[PDB]
Image (cartoon, rainbow, N blue to C red; front, side, top):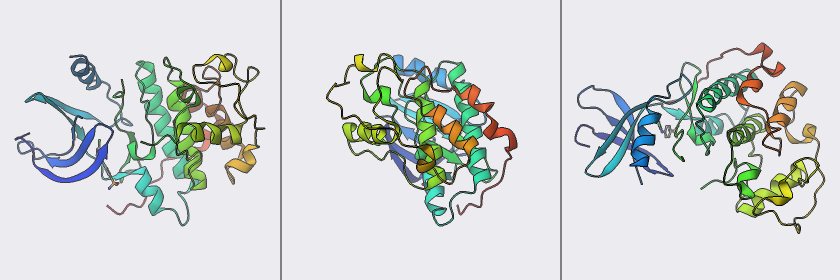
Length: 276
Ligand SMILES: NS(=O)(=O)c1ccc(Nc2cncc(Cl)n2)cc1
């Protein structure tokens, strides 16, 4: 729009390009998302879901039959910071803090029946104060890596539990500095999950064999021990990770119960060292 001035492209998201821009009135620096009546109304509902761990939706501009979303701007995403930190890894107290703030954002959005659906490191925004915020939230109203097994098996009516799964994938990833389930198609994603966690069955996930894309021809893999999966994570963290990675979405821990997990007993808020 004319009221703005792109400083630069800073992403191509699922929903079109993303720009750093300045408001020519306010002088504020914002993130500008160009999209590409229900989308209009649901959008403007999103403008009210405000919280410290949720990137603020500043303004929704429907003009010339286009739809720009103006967000509070942050300088770094977690993918970038994770690469920057690949040599020693993010320190555990900072992994823990990030995990805890994200679970707060999730808890908050979930309490309004709003879900993200597409969590992944690049949607996770960090600042110099040691905060981390969830961006893009509620707008599904290429990466398969963080996708919950119920989405993969063709569940159309999935829950908040899907975000808990993605965040569990991102938690593991921060700890080990490798992607947990780097699938490069839908079946390969599914089968990577099966190989680590065991092919699910009616015992561990009642109803699984009834899902749309479940095939009885699925190979049957035995589950691996978590000590092998996310070392050198302590038994608190692994415990918590296993409850986030439950197959049954009704067994999977809520963001709210996860906040009360013993892992979080010694949580602090360290500050990262960022090169902006
Ligand atoms: N430079 S970076 O890769 O860490 C990066 C890339 C894109 C964005 N995008 C952004 C910034 N503020 C708000 C929103 Cl919604 N998106 C940030 C950092």
